[PDB]
Length: 58
Length: 50
Length: 506
Ligand SMILES: Nc1ncnc2c1ncn2[C@@H]1O[C@H](COP(=O)(O)OP(=O)(O)OP(=O)(O)O)[C@@H](O)[C@H]1O
Image (cartoon, rainbow over all chains, first blue to last red; front, side, top):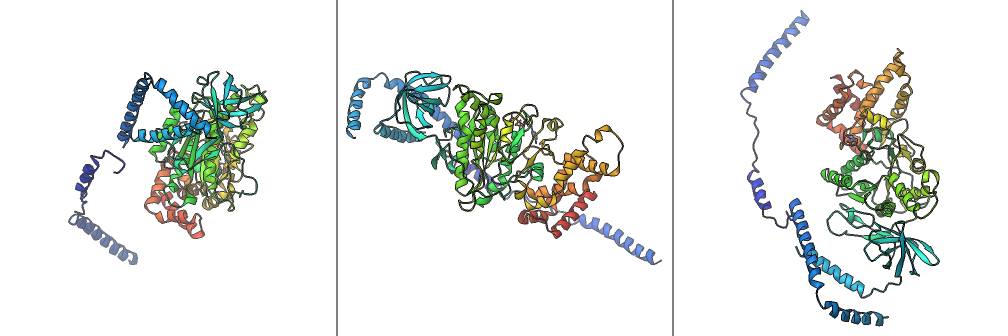
């Protein structure tokens, strides 16, 4: 900022950056749908895991 | 910052053509006469000093 | 505003102060100006190679003295120096401003900056004709100059204080090697240790104005201009400027050499410096030698390149490393000029035109490019995982003309042929992307140990960036190990082999 001797805008866009300093948040919104996908996955997984454990000893 | 450096260059070239204007201002004077006295006293100062 | 007029008025006080002590035990009339050189009567107390100033601003160097008159060569066009003018002598052997304040600036051969960024914050003046350091304050080279190219640090390594030659042909990619090396030194110029920083002085002689303009623009895009020094002697300006400018830049290099720091210099290109020297020796009736370079043109490149080596601990362990560039004529290595730069520098990087015609850029001919004291100063890691690579490319070059017959062969030549083609396509590199040694080790490591052999030949160019991003996202600790240690132990080697075979498997 001390580079520009005729400054006039650096405090303006400085305040513009500090305005948008709470920039924008992300989304860990998935707490309803992702549990459904891991539910189907763990269901099929435990079914297959117990099935092959039975079929090996059979 | 780039535009500031460009504006400094424009100020310097304006004062360069103003230096040309100062050359035109100086060369019409009887400083052409009065300045021979300046060289005279300056040679007095230089050559006496050794 | 008027602030430069303030500064210039202080300089007017200096000029007016200098006018109060101006008594020039020297002045003499210009008898005759001809052949672009001046003969001056008078000046009965001048020195050999003393700087003089004519009455039109064109400076000059007095290079010969005779009983009766003194012969002064010019430093510009002879359009300004008129017959019968006034020749004050400055008082100095030909000197230039040296010191750290030139970093960022673009000067011509006499320290006059032409960037338009004010006067040079000059930490001193130094002679252009400095005697080279003798054989006692020298140490053989033991530190790497990581150029960032793949093939250079694979095959032909550069030590701090090792004068290496970049020889090649016209428009065959000669300047790009030096430019990529300067941009690779950004790895340490941002850092903090002085003894790992490496200042770059690029000395453009004989080139166009606009080429040096684009090169300054390039070194300010990628931010090299906090450590660059451009000495420009562009081909519009007259011949003794080009005869002088690499020497003054070597004085700039010696300033960084004596003061402990390390600095790289690039002469580009000395085949135009010898053009300027044969112009200055064919306008003074000195008779030409072989191919009309005058008989001392070996001595010129000698006394230039010998001001660059590695100082030992007795002088402060500073250094200066030079890359002269030689433009040959059509793949020739046996004209009279390129058989004098080769007989000084410690090796060649022969950028052959035929390989660039096949697009393999940079086009290092491996079987010709060799370095003499490179091997004692490579990074330890590459020397561990490329001790086969020179011999393997020699092996592949053996079967280069044997496979052109199209004859069916055994298994071993097919294996080496596939691995050699993968290595030849592997060493390509785009412009302005030097790879640090921490990333040069795994790519060469994947090349050596046969892991590439299942890949088709066209995927290798994107295999490079894919395997690099695979190591940047996941095995970042291996890259930090190669960065810190600079050496592959057995555990590092096994982890690297696992991390290869992982990404090789898909
Ligand atoms: N790795 C690369 N990527 C892209 N282009 C390249 C690469 N290497 C070289 N070139 C091309 O080579 C051309 C000339 O580069 P360079 O100036 O090094 O050749 P040169 O022989 O040194 O030319 P001159 O001698 O006139 O300086 C450039 O146009 C550039 O596009």
